[PDB]
Length: 563
Ligand SMILES: Cc1cc2nc3c(=O)[nH]c(=O)nc-3n(C[C@H](O)[C@H](O)[C@H](O)COP(=O)(O)OP(=O)(O)OC[C@H]3O[C@@H](n4cnc5c(N)ncnc54)[C@H](O)[C@@H]3O)c2cc1C
Image (cartoon, rainbow, N blue to C red; front, side):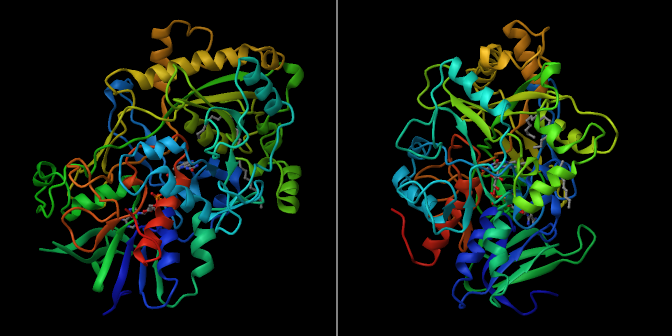
């Protein structure tokens, strides 16, 4: 009742990060009728816009609330895996850190037309940096906002860097400068506009909601993609939910369909629609249009564990928790004043924006990413701690002062999978991250060795002046075997998730999409979101999604070509 006798040149399933990019570029003339279907509501929540309020988006209505299958290798725990549910997708619910990985992350992709040189310019193109001048590696005219964090903990941040210097690390002035090595300590830039989240709804879609050739439907939950037998012909969706009507959106001649549902829901929705492993499709009685075995495999996510240590009594009150909450748990009016009048202060911080990339065992590229947080976790699951920090408000307790080093396997060797658990196209998918399953035990070894690394840093002279013991894992956990068991019961997602519909060369039978993102054996079908990522880069995966999205967009409209 919303696409009524209307045929669209590009239907977009999903209204997230990449989808917000293409809608902008493809609606940019007037000849194309763009449609954008999004399960979740408009982007209007104040919790989206204030960075420190990220503590309220986890496990919230704006999250899909995905939980994984039992992971036997993880002491049989389900893993909560954050996924944004609103226009702007996970860009509106992320920690905003800006990371391209290294040039070798893209060279190693293998694919033709996506080397480090081919992608570099698409990055710069979409960037406007507040803190680096325009050059080979940074843009100034782009739609993304990028800035050095406008919050600084004058004691804990400076003691962290002195400490990482003590244990032998070198600084790194720009983790997205490919001319020098990617390892080292320093400061993560964040996709924020003067302390407001600079999500992709705000930077790309909100400035273009005027275009009459641009139709954006929130509340609109896609169920499948029409593929008359191969050619896609549209989508089916429901505006109310699993108890609503079964509408249909038709495409115009040549009208393509663009999978933007993200690394979790795209491979899922493709399967329900007929493209995937037949063995899995036959189990629920779904006709096979294409039998590509790569749909729903190769799921890569970066696992994390943490250490936590309180500060000495004498330095009580100097953590970021002390800057946001008072001793009674109420939000400080001073912090609100610095944020609303100046775009400064504790509320501009997602917390984890200082850190490092470290080689643990002479690897080609760093295997460990440390994230330092001048706040003290109260649960070894760092995601659950943020949820807890939210509910702590107004209870009347003082959150203890301290620090946290979150440790992350930024280039993991484990892979996962995304599958079908029901025929109900509104059911939670079969999600298995598969952390710690690589055949050499390397991911676990990277995380164990980060624990030793984190303890060295915390033992340094720079940090031992401020610290008083160790809460997590703590004094009991001494031997490697004990560290591993702690890692297993505390491993949490650092929220990347890539690869479930990977691109590859012609004759890559394991590949799903080709180097122009159209999928093997379907007409008018393309995938442009994090799923196409063939190897996860070394860093948080937001920025490369945009780069993919800006790239496909141009290619679609004949402004550049690949190969
Ligand atoms: C909590 C969190 C923290 C993160 N931190 C960082 C970080 O600091 N820096 C960074 O660079 N990256 C970070 N990431 C990752 C980054 O946000 C993602 O990699 C990126 O946003 C993925 O973009 P996408 O377009 O592939 O998917 P999304 O942005 O998720 O877009 C997919 C969209 O599809 C929609 N959808 C799903 N099913 C349907 C359906 N049936 N019908 C219609 N729409 C549907 C979803 O609602 C969603 O809006 C973080 C991720 C999370 C969750």
